[PDB]
Amino acid sequence: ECIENYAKVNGIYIYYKLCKAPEEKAKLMTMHGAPGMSHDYLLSLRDMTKEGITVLFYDQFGCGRSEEPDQSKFTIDYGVEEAEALRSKLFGNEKVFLMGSSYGGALALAYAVKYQDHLKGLIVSGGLSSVPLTVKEMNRLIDELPAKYRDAIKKYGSSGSYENPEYQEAVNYFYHQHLLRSEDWPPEVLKSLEYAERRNVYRIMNGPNEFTITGTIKDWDITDKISAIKIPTLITVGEYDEVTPNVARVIHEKIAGSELHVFRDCSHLTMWEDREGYNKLLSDFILKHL
């Protein structure tokens, strides 16, 4: 069991779990992202503590166990200031590594652009620098789905009938194909998904589901700013990832010296489909840049 607490960061109380390693060779901060509205689905990275890598988990504002601030603060920029306040409060002036998953990756990209001086490295897994590009790419995935499921999405989706039984069925199929492929969904994942359908941030910022984005960040795009990131960067993405490897390619091209890895047979939550290989790829990256 790691250390858990409820600290006041940037105005509201945030929950965090710091899993220290016997020998702290490095510190790693993690940022979850939709559809997973909590750190729970990222606990599989706890294994790295055996490589001398301390891992910090926490629930961002309005998510998981953390309290919800005002709606006017449901922005990526706000999330950036929150992360910096937490990092400083726990590690002071120590430079740490930052890993981001899904929309947490987009958050990690925004953070790096303004605070890269506090990072020794950046890790983006299934992340993105543009929402419009992510939505465009996810629309292609829909058309690649078998007729039955594809027609359910387009039909009931065009009228906003998200409660439709066949619509819900297609969504489940889509996720089991681009979220967590050929694998038994672990409790950690079900927990993070449950938080999404319970809180408000998801619906407000994102929308009904992954391929149906209508929230306040549907226009978010810092592709013309990530080139300013000049630190060792690792980018991972799955072959069948809901956030296509074409989206990752864009990030890989704006960030000089970045490394791109496309995991075959895997999707979005690659840390559960290839737990050993994933953790081994990240730890090796971390240990090479102390």
Image (cartoon, rainbow, N blue to C red):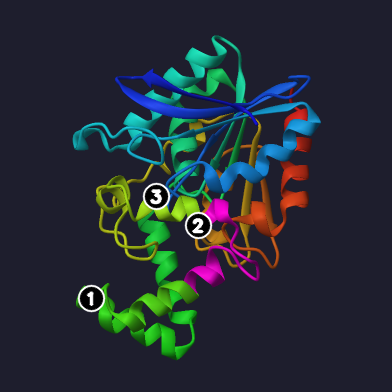
Q: Position of residue 286 (x, y in %)?
A: 73, 31
Image point (25%, 49%), residue name: 204
Furthest-top residue in this view = 93
| In-image side of 239 versus 211 (left or right) | right
Measure the alpha-carbon separation of dots 3 and 1: 22 Å
Label 1 residue SS: loop
Label 2 residue SS: helix
Residue 288 visible to the viewer: no
| In-image side of 210 versus 159 (left or right) | right
Q: Which residue is mark 2?
A: 190
Vertically, is 231 above or below 163? above
What residue range appears in magenta?
174-189
Q: Label for residue 161?
A: 1
Which is more N-terminal, label 2 or label 1?
1
Residue 252 visible to the viewer: yes
Q: Would residue 217 be counted in the magenta stretch?
A: no
Q: Which residue is mark 3?
A: 195
Using the image as rendered, state which of residue 162 and residue 228 is in the foreground. 162
Disc 2 marks which amino acid?
A: Leu
Disc 1 marks which amino acid?
A: Ser
